[PDB]
Amino acid sequence: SSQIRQNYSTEVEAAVNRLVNLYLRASYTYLSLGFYFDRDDVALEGVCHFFRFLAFFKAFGAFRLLKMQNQRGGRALFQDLQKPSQDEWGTTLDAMKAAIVLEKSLNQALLDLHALGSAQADPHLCDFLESHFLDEEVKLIKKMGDHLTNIQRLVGSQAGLGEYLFERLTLKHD
Amino acid sequence: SSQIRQNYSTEVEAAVNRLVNLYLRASYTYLSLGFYFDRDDVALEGVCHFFRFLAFFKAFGAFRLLKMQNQRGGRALFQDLQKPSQDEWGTTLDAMKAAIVLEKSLNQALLDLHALGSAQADPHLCDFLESHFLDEEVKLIKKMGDHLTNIQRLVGSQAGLGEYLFERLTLKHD
Amino acid sequence: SSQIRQNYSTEVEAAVNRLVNLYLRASYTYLSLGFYFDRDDVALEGVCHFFRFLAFFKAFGAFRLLKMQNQRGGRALFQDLQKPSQDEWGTTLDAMKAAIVLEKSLNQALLDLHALGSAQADPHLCDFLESHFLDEEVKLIKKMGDHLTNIQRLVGSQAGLGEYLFERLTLKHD
Amino acid sequence: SSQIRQNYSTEVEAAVNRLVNLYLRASYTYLSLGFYFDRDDVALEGVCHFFRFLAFFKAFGAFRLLKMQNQRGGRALFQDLQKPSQDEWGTTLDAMKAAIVLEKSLNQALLDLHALGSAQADPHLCDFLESHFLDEEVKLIKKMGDHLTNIQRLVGSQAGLGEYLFERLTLKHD
Amino acid sequence: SSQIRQNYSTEVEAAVNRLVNLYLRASYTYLSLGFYFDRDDVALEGVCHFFRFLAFFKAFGAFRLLKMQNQRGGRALFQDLQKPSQDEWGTTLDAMKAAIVLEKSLNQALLDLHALGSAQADPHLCDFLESHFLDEEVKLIKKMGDHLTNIQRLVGSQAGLGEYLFERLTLKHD
Amino acid sequence: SSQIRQNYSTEVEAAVNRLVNLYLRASYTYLSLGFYFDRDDVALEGVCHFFRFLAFFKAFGAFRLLKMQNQRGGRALFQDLQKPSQDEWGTTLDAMKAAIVLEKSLNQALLDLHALGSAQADPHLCDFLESHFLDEEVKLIKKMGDHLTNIQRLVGSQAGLGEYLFERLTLKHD
Ligand SMILES: [Cl-]
Ligand SMILES: [Cl-]
Ligand SMILES: [Cl-]
Ligand SMILES: [Cl-]
Ligand SMILES: [Cl-]
Ligand SMILES: [Cl-]
């Protein structure tokens, strides 16, 4: 079969392809979230920019996984990409909750693939995830949790005021 | 008649003169809105600056239309410029609603003139509007809609606080 | 009434609004003169540029008056802007004569408002006109008189030659 | 409904959403083509880079369409993204033929949407496609046709030699 | 037939080839006008330079049309280029009148090809002409009309003096 | 007749006009060759660029001849420009052979005009050709001969491979 493949199981190869799909689905979800916040009747630029950046970031993750698949002699296989779970995303709070849920699911998938790699004595795979994904993911979830907490603190009798202030004073815009 | 005029109908020539009037009326309306927000008892600099800029922008549009009238061999004809519809403009929300109404009317006038040009097989006219007015107008209306949405989100028990915060954190001032 | 208004009569406030109208009418007249000289069958760029600049200059004068109205606690009130006195402006000589007539009328209006301010013991108003309008106006009328004299000297059996040479050698173009 | 929507038909809105799907599907197809050419048993870097760039370019096209949908007051709706038509793409020639087929299909979709816009008297839509998509698409198809011709000229008894030389001397690598 | 041709009619292809011929004929006419004004017994450098530049400009137009023909998959076909209508071009006025006549004929040909493109639902063709030819042509005809008017104003008892002054003070030389 | 003409025969004047025609015909032939090699089904950029440059170079030669005609007091006379000998130009080899044939014909025409000048004791004419045309022409024919030899060496069982390699490694492209 492959002239380069070594210590690279069919199980890991398949799970890498599945993880690419999950990252591209996440990218697609973030594209939808970003354009929702760009609507004239939502109009929260800082939220749009936050999710738009994550769409690019998740696509980059898929690209890195696909590059690694080839470096190890595996074969990239693509599947249909499921549309995002929602067409409208509600409030900034609703969206940030959905994002944390998505990220925890991606994180569990990274942890599951790491555990498979460990079980299969594939240290290149384990290091790859540890070096390029696990800490990036922990840092992103921490940031979303921080944001969630600030959004929640700003919700009261005055939800619109809080939603505006969060977008203007925490999120990057211009 | 003209040594240069070619494929330039009397109907388009007249409609161009009418459109100049509409743009200058819009400029005048924006001058009034700007100075209203500069009043010591209104005092919203960011709103003043927003409308003052649009007054200049609409005058520029009229200048471009008049330059084109001459480039095509038509004759600029000016009519009286009607005073703005109001002497006092209410809240930022009231003003931004009035501006969107004005812009939609200008947009319909651009679309009507484009349709006349198309019907008269005048592609220079059509391209002129498409290249210098149609997208500029769509972009401006999108921005006003975004602003309207943010102003509306900030209205509640605390309308003054919201009006101040919008002017300070969304609109350009200094 | 106003939290800032002091020593600012209703008569001066009204006369300031009237003077804004006169300056905007003058701006409009200069816009018409400029585009007339831009016609393919007139084609005197230096004359077009001269009047176009005056259109901007007169609008600036109206802006300064409106800013002052607000600084004093008065209320800007806009009226319809009458179309210019002519649709076609004749020769450079005819146009420059019309401009001097317009400027003398604006000057008389400045002098009349100054006299009202003096009579009402409003030195801020008097100084405002003296510092930003009276000398600017005298300088502009002197320049137009100089131009008129040169245009007249160039009129003879060869009026077209003189009109061309004045536009090329006295007026700014490029 | 929308505070900004004007002259924007439901038919165009739906067709824009469909066109976004087509552009994202094209991006996905190009991602697959690129990683196929990055395989250790294919190893044609210049071809990988060509298709990888087109994946980014087609995603950019979808982003521009989605931005426009919002600028016009329409609502972005996403659908499932179908996996590419092939898992393996054959030779450079096979791939370049598949790309031209894909591009002609995207081009027909642009032309169809332009015709709908024209029929609906939507000049903003027509100009948008003309200014940002029609010529870009014609230029890309011309380049692929040029490439196809050069690949074909290099096919003979020595197909591998030709495939290597095309990748090294025509396509960008490093 | 062509691997790239799409939505490109035989009628448009033929009309593009005809238009190339017209632009090259115009270039040739301008070459002749330029060298006539370079004669020692004509000696009007500014007029020579004006027409020489237009010869280059019209050739550039033909080059752009030929590039587009290829981008669309059509086939460039060249025909004999007819010599200019005159061997001697008379006065600057005679020449500028001939140039405006030539330009109006080229403009009508552009408008005719645009109308054919519109009728054939070929928006790439329509946009190409609108973006690279229609406004350039309107601007050039406006300039020639301006020149004609100035030349005419300078004709009187003293035609030679006027012809010299126009060449020295309006046209670019050095 | 001419105030400047001296030692400039009617025979040389006529032959100069004929030579201008030949150079412009050559320019036209090179324009056709260049656009043929730009076809999507030919696609040899380096060959297109080679012939496109020669089209410009031959037009420059005609311009220099026309400038000289005027410097000597002769009168430029233009004739119809015959279309190129072919609509399709075959292979790079076929085209380069046609170009050498064209250049040898231009060279013979230069030599014939030089011999006429010598016979008529017109040393300005002789020097003009020697200084600006004879060596340029010898250098160009040497380059085409070098190219012909390299194209011929690359023709064998693998003509397409050779044609590609010549265009990529000898001719300038980018
Ligand atoms: Cl499937
Ligand atoms: Cl009236
Ligand atoms: Cl009224
Ligand atoms: Cl679904
Ligand atoms: Cl023939
Ligand atoms: Cl003939």
Image (tube, coloured by chain):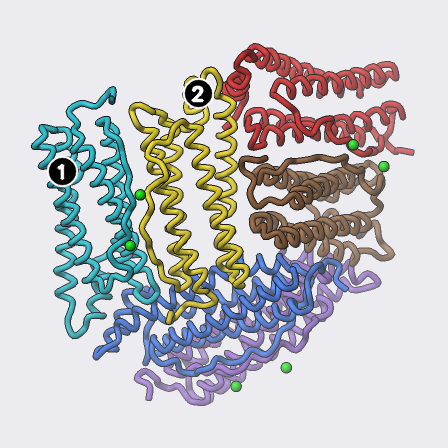
Chain colours: A purple, B brown, C red, D blue, E yellow, F cyan
**Three-letter amino acid code of the residue under disc 1:** Leu
**In this picture, is C68 found above or below D23?**
above
**In this picture, is D78 found above or below F86?**
below
Q: Look at the image and tell me in which quarter the C terminus of chain F lies.
A: bottom left
Crowding near the residue tagged with mark 1, few <14, some 14–19, many ≥20 C-alpha atoms within 10 Å: many
Which dot marks residue E86? none
Q: Which of E80 and B81 is in front in this view?
A: E80
Where does the image place residue F17, in percent across and percent down from the top left?
23, 37
Determine which residue is flagged by label 2: E165
- Left or right placement of residue D137 versus residue F130 in this view: right
**Three-letter amino acid code of the residue under disc 2:** Leu
- Chain letter of mark 2 equals E
Crowding near the residue tagged with mark 2, few <14, some 14–19, many ≥20 C-alpha atoms within 10 Å: some
Determine which residue is flagged by label 1: F113
The Cα atoms of the two marked residues, 2 and 1, are separated by 40 Å
Where does the image place residue A71, in percent across and percent down from the top left?
37, 77
Q: Secondary structure under badge 1?
A: helix
Residue A101 shows in this picture: yes
Q: Quadrant of residue B59?
A: top right
- Left or right placement of residue A132 versus residue C143 in this view: left
- Chain letter of mark 1 equals F
